[PDB]
Amino acid sequence: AAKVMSLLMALVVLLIVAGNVLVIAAIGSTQRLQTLTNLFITSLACADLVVGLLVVPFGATLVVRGTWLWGSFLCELWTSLDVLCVTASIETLCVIAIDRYLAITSPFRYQSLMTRARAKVIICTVWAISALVSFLPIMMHWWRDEDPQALKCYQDPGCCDFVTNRAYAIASSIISFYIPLLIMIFVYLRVYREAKEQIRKIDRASKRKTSRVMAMKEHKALKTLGIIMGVFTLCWLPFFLVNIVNVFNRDLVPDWLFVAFNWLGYANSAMNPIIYCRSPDFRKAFKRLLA
Amino acid sequence: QVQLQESGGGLVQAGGSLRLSCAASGSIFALNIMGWYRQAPGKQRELVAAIHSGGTTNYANSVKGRFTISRDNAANTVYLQMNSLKPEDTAVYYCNVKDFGAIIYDYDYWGQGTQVTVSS
Amino acid sequence: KIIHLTDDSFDTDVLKADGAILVDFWAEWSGPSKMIAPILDEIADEYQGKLTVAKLNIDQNPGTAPKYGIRGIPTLLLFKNGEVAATKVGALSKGQLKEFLDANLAE
Ligand SMILES: CCCCCCCCCC(=O)N(CCO)C[C@@H](O)[C@@H](O)[C@@H](O)[C@@H](O)CO
Ligand SMILES: CCCCCCCCCC(=O)N(CCO)C[C@@H](O)[C@@H](O)[C@@H](O)[C@@H](O)CO
Ligand SMILES: O=C(NCCNC[C@H](O)COc1ccc(O)cc1)N1CCOCC1
Ligand code: NA
């Protein structure tokens, strides 16, 4: 089992780095792909790339070795980098949802409103919020719990467990995950509503001659909308649910499961290249980049 | 397969009017933009007019107040009522459908084109 | 294929013994301790070469169970080169016990 568990972690790093490098390459190398949406995809790909290169590898060792081997400063910095990139990843998914929603439902209002320079500011905000949720509280010890058992892991340089006070785990989880989740639900539900209402008008227009049914395009749109919310929620909801549970009755969920749920969230960073870069232009770019 | 069928073009006198019409057959996602582009000889393809499924519109400045884009409430058909034509409006006019069915990216369909020649 | 352990033979049969030893701490009085008895018999044959099943009656031999801190029964302690590698407590079906062994044996 533990032989297979380490081999699994290896490809998680490979899939993330391979995938996200390939996206960033495709966008930077192809003039056609340098659209406004793909500016946000670039932000996402960078965050997931740093997760693959630095965050997940150091995490892999901690599971295999059973202990932190790089000392207390690098435990903090690795944890800060982890939180930052997960926050920037999830908050960027939320921005993409909004971007696509406006691009689909109000395409003309969107073109004048969403400039490239306004997009650059949105991207910078996401990374600034990510930094202030992660580096500022973790390096300055605001995240620290008072409990004696927690204080034993903070002093031990071999221990790098992710233990926090109440306020931080609530505020950090809401800003990094739950607000982004709700916005994404709200936004994508309005895409479904706008589509459903549009079919109702087409049925009304016919003067009782036809009733529209879900064609090939509508089933694909609904399946695509399912993958987006489904994979995002499956990968991160369990971890972030348990992260709040730990703040109250900490003995309820075992440590091995909470760790396993964290690996599921890291796997999201491998999924995003596959979910968000399926366009014809991306497929042409990927073939060209692989000779 | 999706196909765009263009009609209503041809020769016409300056100050006259045409009514282009593009009937899109096949599965199109309910959220989309049907539009008209044009390519005058030895120039680049420009937008003329576009109408979103919702109802909002977008016109180029050269044709504002003269042209009018509308669409069939029932089927996927888009009309361009061109009034007060000038010799500058002479071009191959292309129908275009931007389909939003993939959510993350838009898929494009182009018609073959239809000639519109405006003489003085 | 099952070794039937005593207090005295425990050092030679389990601690000094080569390979993996699966020790069952059972008692004649416990109903849960009996439910796994016919399952362990099938495990002894199906995991020949990979494991050695062993059994120790707590009524007969009360000295060994205190040393490893056995509260409830049945308790299955998997032994690897004189050390306890993993633990499972309470009764199981054939499939539940196989996943415990399959995961723990193939390192
Ligand atoms: C819309 C953007 C606004 C973001 C701000 C609202 C959510 C986060 C604010 C917040 O911190 N809390 C509300 C979230 O529940 C509560 C926690 O701070 C609270 O648990 C601790 O402060 C106490 O335990 C201390 O006694
Ligand atoms: C460009 C936009 C700039 C906005 C920057 C503000 C970020 C949101 C505020 C914030 O950082 N937090 C909520 C404030 O409570 C999270 C933590 O900083 C804080 O909750 C923890 O430090 C305490 O829980 C520790 O006891
Ligand atoms: O303990 C960690 N890793 C610590 C850091 N992991 C944190 C999660 O990725 C992300 O959480 C948050 C992100 C943003 C937040 O606002 C709050 C939590 N591991 C378990 C062992 O295997 C390696 C990973
Ligand atoms: Na520590």
Image: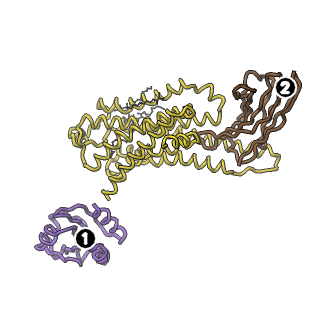
Chain colours: A yellow, B brown, C purple
Residue type, label 1: Leu
Chain letter belonging to callout 1: C
Quarter of the image holding residue A154?
A: top left
User: Considering the numbered disc 2 on the image, is that residue within a helix, a strand or a loop?
Assistant: strand
Label disc, if present, on residue C51 of the rendered structure: 1
Place of residue A119 in the rendered image (x, y in percent of width and height, measured from the top left) = 53, 27
What residue does disc 2 label?
B118
Nearest the viewer among C106 and A28 is: A28
Query: In which quadrant of this rendering is ligand 3 seen?
Result: top left
Quarter of the image holding residue B116?
A: top right
Residue at 69% across, 51% down = A215
Residue at 52% across, 40% down = A182
Residue at 87% across, 30% down = B11
Chain letter belonging to callout 2: B
Q: Mark 2 Cα within 10 Å, few/some/many (few <14, many 20+)?
A: many
Can see residue A179?
A: no
Badge nearest the viewer, 1 or 2:
2
Quadrant of the image for the N terminus of chain A?
Answer: bottom left
Place of residue B98 in the rendered image (x, y in percent of width and height, measured from the top left) = 67, 38
Can see residue C60?
A: yes
